[PDB]
Image 1 (cartoon, one colour):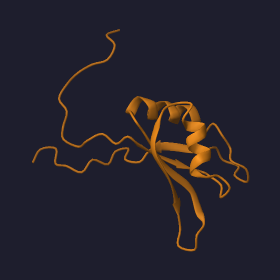
Image 2 (tube, one colour; image 1 turned 90 degrees about the horizontal axis):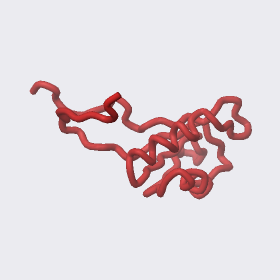
Image 3 (cartoon, helix red, strand yellow; image 1 turned 180 degrees about the horizontal axis):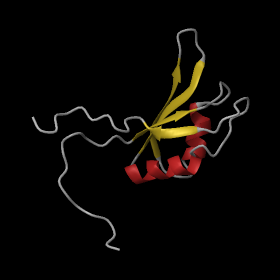
Length: 105
């Protein structure tokens, strides 16, 4: 069961950010960061909003490292159910399969 692996790595970069959804308008950056810190030292946290001024129930959370982020996800992924919402929280990387760059060239 050879743990881990190594191989070629194309140019793209590492996104240490996360995309959270299914949130209410009663939660704030602090709230999350507070419930996220327990998993890892978050670098920066922001909350998405519209024009009028109503949270879209989503926010962006960036961790110091990738591993830390991976945890917070499976840790708070569709596990909680913010009040008012019948669905579970949606936590997933901001750029899942979005790599700006040519494979062949």
